[PDB]
Image (cartoon, rainbow over all chains, first blue to last red; front, side, top):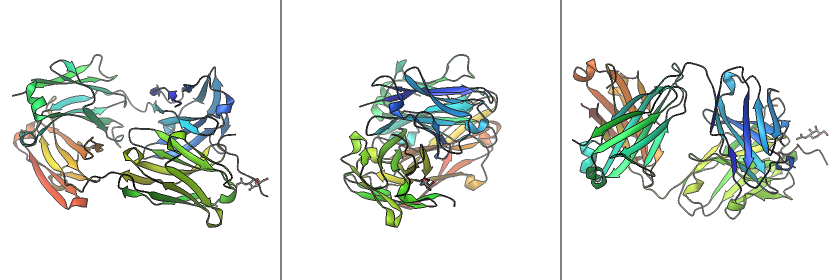
Length: 215
Length: 213
Length: 10
């Protein structure tokens, strides 16, 4: 029952400075919280960067530094490199246990922004013949990674009934693709008529909506 | 000497069962190191499980997990142990042992623990039937299978470019669902046949499915 | 009694 909070995501260009913050729900973050910073690169490669607020793990480059800014813990990456693109987790010490924060996705721009191509797929008639309907929305070849998918049935926003998946960064394109599935009972699916996927990404100046009607 | 924390243990375990994970240290004086266990679950982040001092005088746990895990070590065997008891779905994750050097300094390769009462089930494979600027998108939905993994190919491997097989998601039913997608010229929608070849080895299931407009 | 490597917290 302590929550450590961080920025969802941060975007930078190679050579600029990134500042990540780490907040405690109890109150101010002090040196008695011994803020720890851990990095996760793709394929679950974890690296310890900082421990005890300020102490670097030996051999970690000095361009990573830990500090306190006001009532929070902070990791600063000065001159962030393409190599530093990763998820950064902070852990705060609370007397007898560590709590990790939810992590921050730091992007180091290696290419131009690419708007996703958005496609929508209605349930197959085969899957309908069983008691389930799944509508799939595909966001194809977009950069950077940050994207939002909203599902809407007859103009109504949905919740708790969708799950999404993302590919790893493409070898060639540096892009991502995303697949979101909305699952309904064949009855729930046949009760309403219009199924809509709303996509927000930085390469789209306004949200894109892909929609189909039943039949 | 190159350092290495070699982990062993893990796998699929039924709700309420118990597991023991081992972490053998190589290349350091294991005897003078604080050791710790953390875990990484799909929708969650890193979660700290606990730590133990080199002499085992002190063993600290996360309050929410202290009645489920037991950390121990045998310095003569250079090994650290994590004992899991009465496990539940939320314990599904990759578990890591870490060596403290001013921070989480040294890490093991990770051990996957999957907690589920689900039975082996082959997937059902539904089409994702097809358009953007002469480009069309089609695919297959590989739904309701257990356990992981699944493999997906297109046209027996002859089709590869423009292919994205996505990570599976775990549904509330306890079964996995996965999607595989390909973009192609829409020219081709009527002069090429597209088939996805799905292999779920755990259940000896192989299904070929044609995607048509 | 040998040393102890510095822990991630104090």
